[PDB]
Image: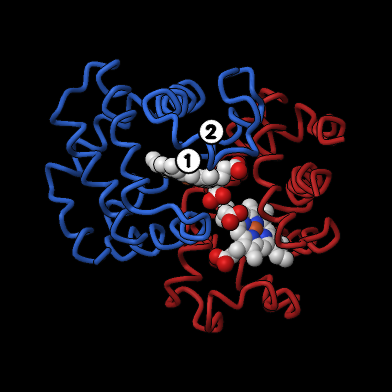
Chain colours: A red, B blue
Amino acid sequence: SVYDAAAQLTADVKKDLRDSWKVIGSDKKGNGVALMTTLFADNQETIGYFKRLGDVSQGMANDKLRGHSIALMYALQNFIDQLDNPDDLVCVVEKFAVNHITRKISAAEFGKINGPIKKVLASKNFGDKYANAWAKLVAVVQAAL
Amino acid sequence: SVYDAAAQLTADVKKDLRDSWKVIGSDKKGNGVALMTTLFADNQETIGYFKRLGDVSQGMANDKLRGHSIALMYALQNFIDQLDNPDDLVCVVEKFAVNHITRKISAAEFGKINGPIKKVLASKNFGDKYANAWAKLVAVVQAAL
Ligand code: HEM
Ligand code: HEM
């Protein structure tokens, strides 16, 4: 199932992913927090999964939120680095899904991160073309949930 | 405390961590697996914590082990990248510790990784100087467990 989803990651998709990541991944703390705060602003219900982070309204200033946001970006860094070898991408994605499955995060719920990604990309001037590429990567993870 | 341990990362310690990581971090899949296989060989008692990975002796051929090993290297990548800002290093370390605390991994248990790191470092021509530098980094995580 995950292998099949990985099949949608074509040469053009992987190229747009790497190109956009070169910019987005250059400021992990800044963009990581931007992603999380956008998620919470657009889909307030998702906050229920993050009680441990405390007062998420503090954004960057919240050490726990900042710490989680940075770690999140290194997962994406991992995914991007494994794009040229489906076997490694798959094992890394499945490894990654384990904890989210335990937290009872469904594929539909996980898909809520697409809006935030689209907006973060746009803030850096990466249009719909890139947004669609990232939706495909997220789709690989969704297949593992 | 983790704050006091983080202050032990002096200028030269940070430099030796970077110089050595530049090499070790070049092959995350290869060195990550070697790191885990060495841990399981020198400390068989830790294998119990990794029941989910299945047959750990298969090494590289074990998809779950390969996935975990890669993820492990990106956590180290994360730590290395945060060396410039103590505040960020701390929040990333505490975030990382959460899951290990949940699995009941004590500071003494975590410290067993020092052996494997020293051996991998040595296999790449990095001696005691570097192994001790990494022990310092590991000690930051230990202070958070
Ligand atoms: C591309 C998007 C995402 C990435 C790359 C990502 C990455 C991560 C990473 C690396 C961790 C830390 C390791 C772990 O405990 O598994 C984590 C933890 C977590 N993730 Fe995800 N995640 C994403 C989206 C989501 C979404 C959409 C939700 C919620 C609806 C979610 C909920 C959680 C929770 C609850 C934790 C634990 C937070 C804490 O208490 O520190 N994740 N995620
Ligand atoms: C250089 C030291 C280490 C690093 C950087 C590291 C890194 C990681 C990472 C990134 C994960 C995946 C995210 C998560 O679930 O928290 C993890 C999982 C885990 N770690 Fe650590 N770890 C280290 C040492 C250890 C040691 C020494 C033990 C136990 C003796 C341990 C036990 C575990 C276990 C049981 C898991 C879950 C494995 C699975 O079910 O896939 N870790 N670790």
Q: Quadrant of the C terminus of chain B?
A: bottom left
Q: Could you say whether the residue bearing mark 2 is in a helix, strand or loop?
A: helix
- Quadrant hosting residue B76: top left
Q: Is residue A116 visible?
A: no
Q: Nearer the viewer, residue B114 or A82?
A: B114
Residue A101 in the image: x percent, y percent? 74, 54
Residue A85 in the image: x percent, y percent? 67, 23
Q: Quadrant of the N terminus of chain B?
A: bottom left
Residue A81 in the image: x percent, y percent? 58, 33
Above or below residue B137? Residue B125 is above
Identify the mark at residue B70; answer none if there is no mark: 2
Q: Are marks 2 and 1 in contact (CB under 8 Å)?
A: yes
Instruction: Tell me: B55 left or right of B84.
Output: right
- Quadrant hosting residue A32: bottom right
Cβ at disc 1 under 8 Å from ligand 2: yes
**Chain of the residue under the numbered disc 2 shown in the image:** B
Disc 1 marks which residue? B74
Task: Give the CA separation, mark 2 to mark 1.
Answer: 7 Å
Amino acid of disc 2: Ile
